[PDB]
Image: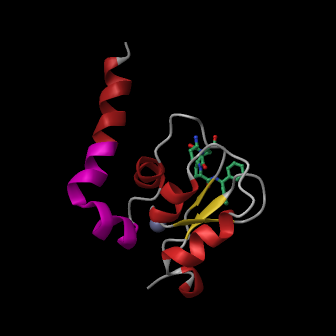
Amino acid sequence: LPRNPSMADYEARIFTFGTWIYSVNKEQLARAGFYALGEGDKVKCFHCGGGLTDWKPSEDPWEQHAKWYPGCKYLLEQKGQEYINNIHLTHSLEECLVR
Ligand SMILES: CC[C@H](N)C(=O)N[C@@H]1C(=O)N2[C@@H](CC[C@@H]1CO)CC[C@H]2C(=O)NC(c1ccccc1)c1ccccc1
Ligand SMILES: [Zn+2]
């Protein structure tokens, strides 16, 4: 049920990062199901349509995917039920832990 059948394959996705000036890894992004829109560092997940932008140095493409778009069927089969929930518990723990 992918929102962009043309961007379904990895090859088509890194193809979009031919002018990537940002330090977030292009191969990592492509593998997480993202491609670029030539509009700042904005990226769209090929399958869920989920859009991410303003990446920070410490930010894992997979982790960011699960943080904002956990419904994603592509994410689920790549990384798993437990992975997705874990990322959410981690943010739940941190906020609780920080006084
Ligand atoms: C990707 C890691 C980054 N540090 C981050 O968390 N970005 C957030 C984000 O992309 N979104 C979350 C909140 C804003 C954050 C930026 O401070 C909610 C969902 C997501 C989003 O939809 N971003 C938008 C967008 C567009 C313009 C300005 C701000 C956010 C978006 C929409 C379409 C395509 C790309 C990004
Ligand atoms: Zn997705």
Quarter of the rendering occupied by the N terminus: bottom left
Q: Which residue lies furthest to the left in this view?
A: 82
Q: Is the magenta stretch mostly helix, strand or loop?
A: helix
Span highlighted in magenta in the image: 72-87
Residue 78 location, quadrant = bottom left
Residue 96, compared with residue 16, is above or below; it is: above
- Of 56 and 98, nearer the camera is 56
User: At x 54% / y 76%, what residue is drawn?
Assistant: 11
User: At x 37% / y 35%, what residue is drawn?
Assistant: 91
Q: Is residue 77 left or right of residue 28?
A: left
User: At x 46% / y 55%, what residue is drawn?
Assistant: 65
Residue 75, compared with residue 10, is above or below; it is: above
Magenta stretch: residue 76 in it? yes
- Of 65 and 8, nearer the camera is 8
Where does residue 21 sit, x and y in percent of width and height? Answer: 73, 49
Quarter of the rendering occupied by the C terminus: top left
Where does residue 30 sit, x and y in percent of width and height? Answer: 52, 64
Where does residue 63 sit, x and y in percent of width and height? Answer: 41, 48
Q: Is residue 32 left or right of residue 46?
A: left
Where does residue 62 sit, x and y in percent of width and height? Answer: 42, 53
